[PDB]
Amino acid sequence: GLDIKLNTAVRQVRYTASGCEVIAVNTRSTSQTFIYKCDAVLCTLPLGVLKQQPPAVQFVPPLPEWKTSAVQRMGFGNLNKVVLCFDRVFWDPSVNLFGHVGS
Amino acid sequence: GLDIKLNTAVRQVRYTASGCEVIAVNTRSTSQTFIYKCDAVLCTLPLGVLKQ
RNA sequence: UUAG
RNA sequence: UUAG
Image (cartoon, rainbow over all chains, first blue to last red):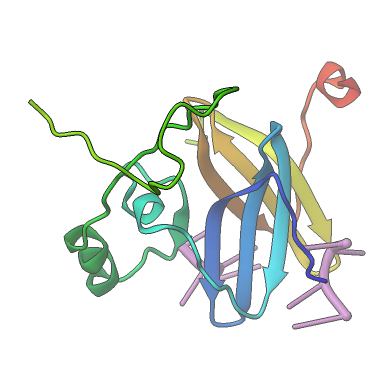
């Protein structure tokens, strides 16, 4: 029921006394540009994106120091997973999970 | 004596009743965006570009 | 969307 | 350039 523009990468957020405009591009062809005008912007960008230097998203005017300083101090961690698909089960099905100790 | 922004590729020209805004990018890093606001735009783009 |  |  929501209006969602997929494949739309925000590039710049402009926020002013009179309103906001958000500049985004098509991810499938980055030349194609869109300008979304609104009363307010809700930023949901991951902290990792906000941390990115040089910026992946530019804020105009620049965010105040008390905001940027916080973005720098906070940690943004990492963890990954490997999916292994087999045709046969060869492990104990009753065991939800088991470990492996490193050398 | 002129103000020239080199390495600035215009991507979109917006022209309205109240004025114009021109969206351009840095050719050396196309993520970096600029919005130039003005009363009028003079288009000097080659016919080949306009045909593209 | 020449945002309403 | 939160165009003036």
